Image (tube, rainbow over all chains, first blue to last red; front, side, top):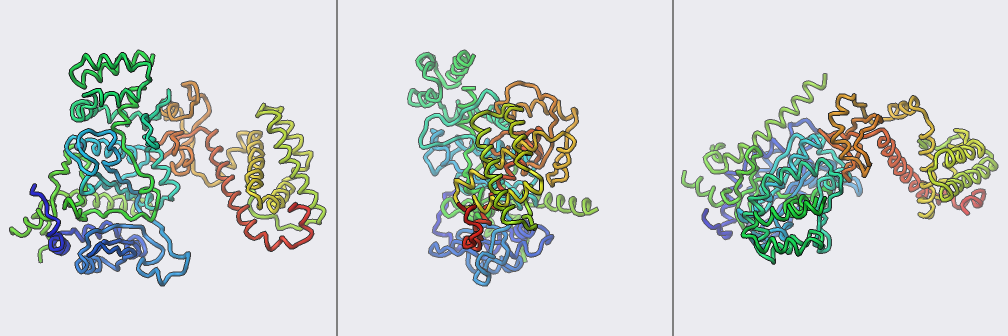
Length: 389
Length: 213
Ligand SMILES: [Zn+2]
């Protein structure tokens, strides 16, 4: 796509916020169906304006406020927070210790820079097709646990706009989880003990918890192509020593030779398996995990008041739109073909309206968001109409 | 279940005495603690000879407990010490209890659990056995297992010491209790906090100096 010029941002945002931002769908979601007092009215939004000024306890009465206000402030950034005991903007009106964060979707944030020690392709803040597989594996490992382990049914996965993804778990029961539990969910999914620069970072015990097992599996299905072909983790001494490090020193010199007498990583990996297998008679799995398993930041998920990047917001540098990822075609998701605020504004230009976004490249993405919404409606209609019986 | 302070009234002697009697029982949990091990009846019966002998008896254990709160709600070493022996005692009280009455306190409680039939048991035996601690063996024994909301098992699943499936934790009855106990330690701790909080409105009283010292 055309390289984006962040100088046009002010104008693009104005257009974007007045004709393309999926307001009605954004509202349909955050209002969760009017099944609760002021669930929406008590939702905190945060904004990053003009000179990078940071406004925070913003609130709104209905969908129309949200539109009016946004269009007047044309936010460079928009963040979503918790649902409070009182309308956020009236916190000067609320007593001390009475104003509190009560409900909020469980969220996760996965960033490629949290893997800089396991990727040879790009540089820290960048991403390429060779490292994006990690986001693919992250989404599958994490989304499987949330669904099969915790029974969470509503999970909205979203592209961060540059080098990562976010996940918003919205189950009505989940929005009520205590921080202690969230903090626990994160620990249950965490496996890479990224200590103060400690070479080895994963240790399995003879026994293997099923979550770990099912995780190893998913990884297995991409390891070769991603790790052996794309990353070529065993290409040199400067690379395989890095992997040798995660293996008992009594095995170094042997493998060091096999590696030396090999021609590619797919070969060397196969030697590593063979040799390590003798010794063992888990070393393998640990290496795959240390290179492919997601790294989650406990902070993002622990706090119930955490303000996170809003879906459909615009990335200041890359210009990409924060679009919902379609789980049924995760592997197919391409960060590089993600519509730019510039790109979509141009499409609009080359053409009330209310279906304007549908004539843009956002269309498919907002479609995904709608299905996500249709299911919410169900669960809601399901539980109430069938259980309030 | 040491909630709801005794509203009754007792002589300064009752108070004065009880305190010392408990300070002894827990002091005994200190003895039967480093001299033995949870070596069945030895550590057991010995503890249960103190139990009845030293008085506690239910209404007696009740008052005794609370009165000692006023005591150890000051030094953290105390609060940790007090909550300590106070626990080993609550476990003991369970141990003995028969399967019949045990089931009551579980239900009569609030925790929403269920027992699984050998049906799901063997089907998940595999998983369950793998979720467990270093728990040697590959047999899901005969000890029945229960299905409780994953949240209620927080201290278990956050360390992957149990199997979650569809938002439920599948645990042995040994573990359901272990949960209820940490819930105790916790609730109690909240109480010692509140007592110390309003201790000041009782420091000045003279009748209470032997105790607080
Ligand atoms: Zn890369």
